[PDB]
Image 1 (cartoon, rainbow, N blue to C red):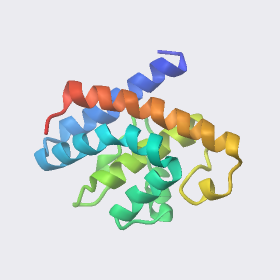
Image 2 (image 1 turned 60 degrees about the vertical axis):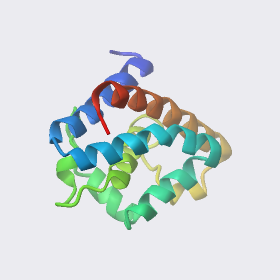
Image 3 (image 1 turned 180 degrees about the vertical axis):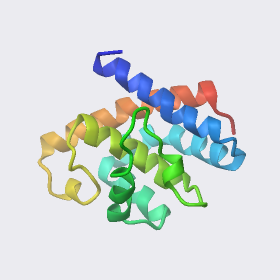
Length: 146
C-alpha cells in the first residue's frame, strides 16, 4: 500500500468499514445508495455541483464541514464520531471526498475554493474524486447492504 491506487483502495476500505461498524441500518442503506450514485453524479454534473448538492442536502456550510475535518487527525480517519446524534449520509460522503482531496490534491479544496481555482486543478480534483468514489462504490457493494 504505497502507490496512489493502493492508498485509494485502503482508504475507501476504512471509511466504508466505519459505516458498517456503526451498525445503523438506516444510515448504512441511505449511504450505500448515495455512494453508488456519486461517481455518476460527478461525471454528468461535475465536482463543484455534486459537493454543493451534498452540503445543501445536509443543510450545512463548507465552514462547518472544514471545522469537522480539522478534527480528523488520525489514520485510519474517524468521521462518523465527529458528527452529531444525527448522522447525515450526505455530509458524511462530503467529508469522505473532501478529506481525500485535501490530502492528495490540495489542502484548501472545498465548495467555495472550487469556484475560483484554475481548470487544471478542478479537472485533477474531479478525476481524483471519481477514482476515489469508484473504490468506495466497489467496497460498499462488497461490505454494505440496503
